[PDB]
Length: 131
Length: 349
Image (cartoon, rainbow over all chains, first blue to last red; front, side):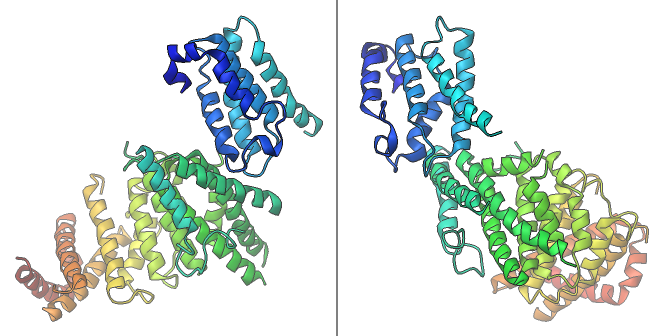
């Protein structure tokens, strides 16, 4: 929808997307916020968006930032779960990291990406804690 | 492609779901599907991958093949299951109960064969095999060692999987795959089953496309791998093969010969000596057809095979200036073959 909405997505703005982000899986996270049935697939639609990493495509940077914040929230929401794969998450994270590098190449502020970078530090810190 | 490709991926998942799609197994996946905990996690990932495969879909591509990341993920999980089957083969390699472990490995191999059918169904699973350890997949290389080591049927399934992989594989990738067969040809035996040998012949046709196997030649006789395989084909004991199935193995050899004939590149060669013996074996089959003198579909297939055999015999006469020297070894057969050729001309309509 966000690519399709275009100027209408700009008319919807970051807030209609933010309201959806607030509505689902926001802050509380846990098993209840994310459907067991959605499982990887709810993450996978986000992962496909992460794979596109289209911050530039979105008409509004703030809407893109809200989507990036939602992705950062999704990473905070993400906890290892049945039907969720850390390697799949790492591949999504790698797609997110490439998107983050593109945002880094042209970002006025780290903004949501700095929150994503903190999420990037998380798990990588766990890998440092182990490996 | 698109949703229809995803449905084809789902159909491959449905075949894995079906108990068992593989022959000789009561159940496929599920209890048969299931560190051991890591393998269980991989099996859950494979189920997620199967759900992902349902959700999402030149010459090496061949017919366009749907590619699913989940199918590739399932293939990695399948590789872990294959690794458990490989570990039983590795334990057998270490050895100088275990059969039950081999039976569990065989069920895993049957699952791997179902996975290989799924790999034929899904490009991404094939692509992961194509990338390999760095080439041959590390699990696949272990499987190739296992194939060298029921078990013969699993090896035949692996050879069939290799032939499917070879069609998926780029000819340069197939050449890197090629020469695995030369070790396999040494593994292949008259004692080893003819149906397995027919799968090897299908693998040999895939090998003929591969450049390294194409570099391997009938010339150099017994030392040449192709000639030695032809010599086994020339014996044609076919003890495992029965009736049409024995004819089908001969027909597969004829198709492989036709592929060699199509190729521009294709005694001194055991295979050339074998080809006169093979022509005599074809003549014996032709004599049976002459004795039959095509209402049965198998009989109709045999008549087409006899027409193919006659074309191969015509090609063999074109191939050798000394057609007569080859003929003199097969001359008692050749007089029968000439009667058979007249019967074949009568058969042609």
